[PDB]
Amino acid sequence: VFDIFELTGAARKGSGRRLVKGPDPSSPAFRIEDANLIPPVPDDKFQDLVDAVRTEKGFLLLASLRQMKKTRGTLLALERKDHSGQVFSVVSNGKAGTLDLSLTVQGKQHVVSVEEALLATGQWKSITLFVQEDRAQLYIDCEKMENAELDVPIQSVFTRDLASIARLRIAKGGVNDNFQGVLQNVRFVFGTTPEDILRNKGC
């Protein structure tokens, strides 16, 4: 389990946020004000995560969010240290009503949309994103699964060197995709299945 907000240390480090209330009463919720001021995930931490994806050939990402209507907000993104772009990002697109998965491999950027994933209602929603090999499975709360196939296997982006040329940034998008709203419990979980999470929360 990699809890992004916990790792970046945003609860007691940097700005860009206001600790508020979230569905989970036992952990912080962050209303995003300026995504560039939230510290990134330290590199020793990001590479730990990269190794875990490296191993599972994928990951299970969890997140609760309360996004503003009709907006495109970025849950998280791997931005290159040599300031130019992202190598991977997850965007809740309230204009298309999709969850976009973007992977840039060797100067080639690929984007696929998971359809019928409207999360940009101005109310709390929990997602369970399961990515393995080139397959993406999304469960919003307890409603039925939505699918999408990547153009390239997820681990191909998650290379062994990843941490030294890029850093993991939460809520921060690409010039017009910073998350507008509140986020809670953004986490990468390994060795578990989406079915276990679905039951582990009463579906």
Image (cartoon, grey):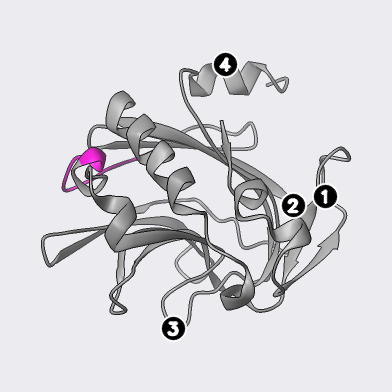
Residue 87 in picture, x, y percent from top left: 28, 61
- Residue 34 is a magenta residue: no
Q: CA distance from mark 3 to mark 1?
A: 27 Å
Q: CA distance from mark 2 to mark 3?
A: 25 Å
Proximity of marks 4 and 1: CB atoms separated by less than 8 Å: no
Q: Which residues are magenta?
A: 147-155
Q: Nearer the viewer, residue 141 or 15?
A: 15
Residue at label 1? 22
Q: Is residue 84 above or below residue 113?
A: below
Identify residue type, mark 4.
Asp
Q: Residue at x 57, y 16 (%)?
A: 196
> Residue 196 got which mark?
4
Q: CA distance from mark 2 to mark 1?
A: 8 Å
- Residue 150 is a magenta residue: yes
Q: Secondary structure at mark 1?
A: loop
For residue 115, side relative to residue 85 (left or right): right
Residue at label 2? 124
Identify residue type, mark 3.
Val
Q: CA distance from mark 4 to mark 1?
A: 22 Å
Proximity of marks 2 and 1: CB atoms separated by less than 8 Å: yes
Q: Residue at x 33, y 52 (%)?
A: 163
Residue 202 in picture, x, y percent from top left: 73, 20
Sooner in the amino-acid sequence: mark 4 or mark 1: 1
Which callout, 2 or 1, points to the residue nearer the camera?
A: 1
Which callout, 3 or 4, points to the residue nearer the camera?
A: 3
Q: CA distance from mark 3 to mark 4?
A: 36 Å
Sooner in the amino-acid sequence: mark 2 or mark 1: 1
Identify residue type, mark 2.
Trp
